[PDB]
Length: 299
Length: 299
DNA sequence: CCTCGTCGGGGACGCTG
DNA sequence: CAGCGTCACCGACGAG
Ligand SMILES: [Zn+2]
Ligand SMILES: [Zn+2]
Ligand SMILES: [Zn+2]
Ligand SMILES: [Zn+2]
Ligand SMILES: [Zn+2]
Ligand SMILES: [Zn+2]
Image 1 (cartoon, helix red, strand yellow):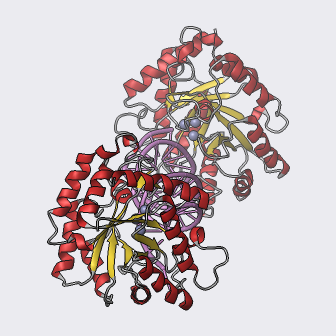
Image 2: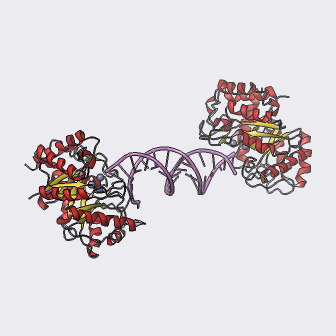
Image 3: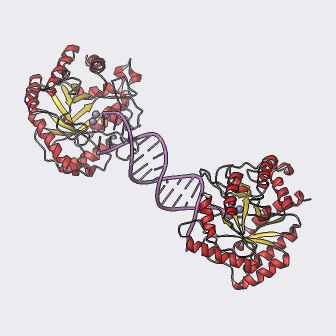
């Protein structure tokens, strides 16, 4: 197999109005159907199992059982984005760490392959401190997502900072820790990835530290951005419709995105499209454009 | 007689170099002599009897006796500008109100006809509340000077606010309260008085509330301004040398200043020229220019 | 139970009448 | 003392 492409599945916008106990499983079912209809069978997906605005578990025991069968039936590589309250490097991180411990156990329970956590603009020593309090579970790897700020030293969007972080992780013998790369986050953090060569040099530098972070522990969030490079604002957009790759609307194979797609296919990485909008028709309209553009890129 | 013109007499820049014995009286003598020399006998004067940077009485009992004889000898109309600490409507409204009682009693002791107090950017009732705490002394009237601010609500530079303020004063029947109009203060407070008619309508509006504030209790600070209209900055300048009446350097009888002089001559008001320069040579140079300009205006 | 950014109001400051 | 300009800080507010 090559790359494993997919999108973020909102419970609201994908679950059938008449679900009762297995709502998350139903949202996946319609999501899988949508891909087969548009001619792009998905191999990956991202969902919420909690929050994301409150540290509360959303899934139900009925949904757990049927979700595992749904994932195995369609051979899906699924991660769960943690709630926005998941910051192990905080003051009262005793509740938070236990809450993440719960999410990790559920992911193993239902066949989800990881949990995405946001990185703070904090020194790497504090990050591993919070990570040290988390006892891991097998089969589930914590993915650390690239943050987005403006006037903070620690951005974790340059390779020098990513290496230094994961070097401390490897020196601490911390198991099952990965990296999630959000193109919009590193772009709103100062890293210009518009042209093929600029994304090339960045990805080449990522490959140069594979001993610290191997591509087996790397996933991608393929997002365009409706903001400026270095602004520090998270405003996702559909591919080639935001300020990163809008200029490459009719030369898509010269864009920094195609260089990312080449990396994803080369290292068989997961790629998630996190874009949310007001309506189901609006979302499936944008998703049809993006995934048909990927279909042409993989043709 | 007509108007009573004069200037502010610093008891340093006018007293004999290194004065010790009766300095305020000596400063007046040279000030009177300076007028006789330049051909402009002064009828008014303004001095400090305290501060203005510290709540301490500067005059001495020796100076008191000779100053009274000096004032009567030349028939001078003298006021004392209060220190910058004189705010009866403040937190320390117990100490300040007693300090003013001291200054007020000294003015009667030496023949000074009033004390100038600055108005705050405060509601008018706090002002009369503070003024009600002051037991008056006869023959001495408290003159309230117009302030200078940009963003505060209360400017006391438009006639609508002056009227309600002094209306509040008359309704409380507290005696011996006057008004001091600083052309530079009301100008840096938003009131353009550059042209003859603009000063005309403002002074005309002052005459319209003569039942509330009679011209017998009105004095003037004739200052140009080295700032912009409405800036909120107190920067005095010589007449026709600042940003108010510089445009009327060779058409002085078409300026708003001449309209003020007409008012002063009409109601026999005192007019004080407050100039802060560097040396005695700098000050007496600027004063000769202004007072000779007034000499031509009164010809 | 988290953080980003922005925006807009509050107080601190070393001036100057 | 009470003005101003300047500006950082705290506290709301939508984000994701
Ligand atoms: Zn995220
Ligand atoms: Zn993301
Ligand atoms: Zn994002
Ligand atoms: Zn004054
Ligand atoms: Zn004045
Ligand atoms: Zn002034």
